[PDB]
Image 1: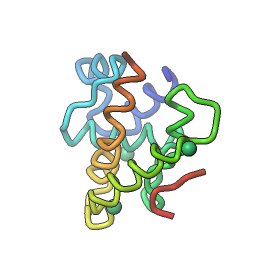
Image 2 (image 1 turned 180 degrees about the vertical axis):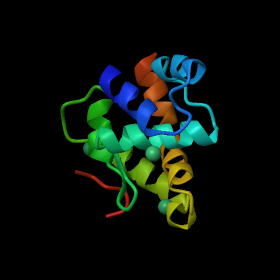
Image 3 (image 1 turned 45 degrees about the horizontal axis):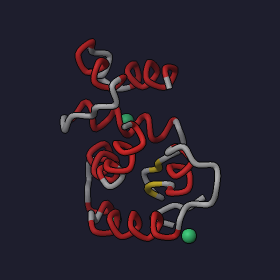
Image 4 (image 1 turned 120 degrees about the vertical axis):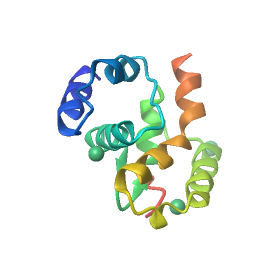
Length: 119
Ligand SMILES: [N+]
Ligand SMILES: [N+]
Ligand SMILES: [N+]
């Protein structure tokens, strides 16, 4: 939402940038260090993500326009995607969050057009 975008743009060094914010409001998240930290911030703020427990799959399911229990195949597919990314070995917390969210890229794009993965 608007609120979390403005707050994270202030929280993250470099993110209060006109050009990046145009992308962010268009749901476009480039692979750059500032945007890495921005994506982490939004995930933390919306309770979609956690540095330790990873991606909250039920929370994201709901953020994809659903009010019910996540489909089993949605959970399975993303748990597997996230495990394959070996997130625990990614030392940079922003890079780790960005890499995590890449698993859910296709879902968010389709939509636009607790079930922690690491319990
Ligand atoms: N962040
Ligand atoms: N299911
Ligand atoms: N992982």
